[PDB]
Length: 115
Length: 114
Image (cartoon, rainbow over the protein chains, first blue to last red):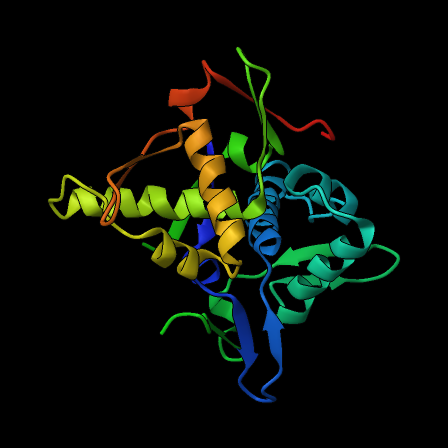
């Protein structure tokens, strides 16, 4: 395939608000592209031998962005805070990409700049 | 639509280099998102019977990012320089969205890091 898919809600939103706590998580532009890439990769790992997704954050950010290490950590933390990416394990760690659909009971995506 | 599409080359590249002039256009993340959005919007305008895609740059930038006026001007310039967007008129200006494939004879996409 010659295209990645960018989730409609994510593209059109600049933040997510926790429905239980009110916490506000800004959504950065890089995060949206990183999510699109990881979703595709997760699906490719599944298709090609049904492997769990273990691509390193470093490799992921090298493909999608050109940012400082400190920034990369912030962007990765947006993803994990929202639950779009779930890191499971420590010794045999892997990454699970979750749909936006699956976290809406917890996170309400909005665009505070639209009147 | 449930999702917007972004060309593989665009997502995986951090710069475009003009094959004839050497000019380099770094590909900001916002640029990629704005392009994906505008490509779909252009398609929807045409699907609903319109010849022209007339959404304003201000509305476009409001939906896709949260950046200051000067940055929006520069991001729009990244797009017009590449020829991915062609702008016609002053106020109420319509925008023609071209494919990445239509510009590769002029611009080479790369990821120096990758």
